[PDB]
Image (tube, rainbow, N blue to C red):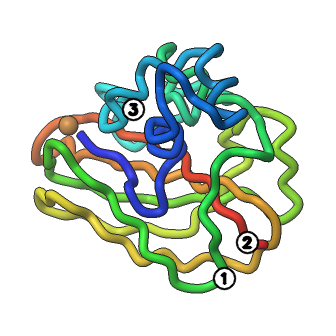
Amino acid sequence: HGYVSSPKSRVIQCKENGIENPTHPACIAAKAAGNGGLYTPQEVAVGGVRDNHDYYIPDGRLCSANRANLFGMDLARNDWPATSVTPGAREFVWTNTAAHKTKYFRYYITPQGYDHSQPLRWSDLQLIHDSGPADQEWVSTHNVILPYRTGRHIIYSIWQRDWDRDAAEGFYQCIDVDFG
Ligand SMILES: [Cu+2]
């Protein structure tokens, strides 16, 4: 159980903007599509997953991990609240509510030119970081090297719980960033 707190993931950006009465236009939209999962940002979860996330999560459902109460997270928008980034090293931090033995934390990113016009697909993601396995960590920090980009981008971090040492389960976090 956990989520990316820094840069704030999309479920955290919108949580903090107000789940019941959001004011930001993307989160207002997310409310209408399914956002009551925003109370439990640590749970964008899939049970049984063993490094085969695309079997369990359909394209267009990467941000909700296909959970309906987060379907608002699946909307294509160029106005998601985003953190300013630049190419090079950026810390990404997972705040874990319940620690687990870890096969890996991985990060992916959209390609240069990405236009936010369709929901996020597996084919949209390039691997940009792999943290390797870990023991339990209350806080998991990955210094991800951001490739050259301009414009707004989506980062997808994925937490694979170590199924050999522990249990099979996946946690999924879409983060919005802006390369300027
Ligand atoms: Cu957990």
Q: Earlier in the sequence, mark 1 or mark 2?
A: 1
**Type of amino acid at the residue the image marks with label 3:** Val
Q: Using the numbered discs, state the Cα–Cα distance from disc 1 to disc 2 in whole angstroms.
A: 8 Å
Residue at 84%, 54% (x, y): give it.
Answer: 114
Q: Quadrant of the N terminus?
A: top left
Which quadrant of the picture is home to ligand 1?
top left
**Label 3 packing within 10 angstroms: few (<14), some (14-19), many (20+):** many
Q: Is residue 111 above or below residue 76?
A: below
Residue at 17%, 36% (x, y): give it.
Answer: 167
Position of residue 136 measured from the top left corner of the image (x, y, whole percent): 11, 57
Q: Is residue 15 left or right of residue 54?
A: left
Q: Residue 87 carries which label?
A: 1
**Label 1 packing within 10 angstroms: few (<14), some (14-19), many (20+):** few
Q: In this view, does 24 lie above or below 104?
A: above
**Residue wearing tag 3:** 44
**Type of amino acid at the residue the image marks with label 1:** Pro
Position of residue 70 measured from the top left corner of the image (x, y, whole percent): 51, 23
Q: In this view, does 41 lie above or below 31?
A: below
Q: Using the numbered discs, state the Cα–Cα distance from disc 3 to disc 1 in whole angstroms.
A: 27 Å
As helix, strand or loop, the secondary structure at mark 3 comes to loop
Residue at 67%, 77% (x, y): give it.
Answer: 147
Q: Which mark is residue 179?
A: 2
Q: Earlier in the sequence, mark 3 or mark 1?
A: 3
CB within 8 Å, label 1 to label 2 = yes
As helix, strand or loop, the secondary structure at mark 1 comes to loop
Q: Residue 110 carries which label?
A: none
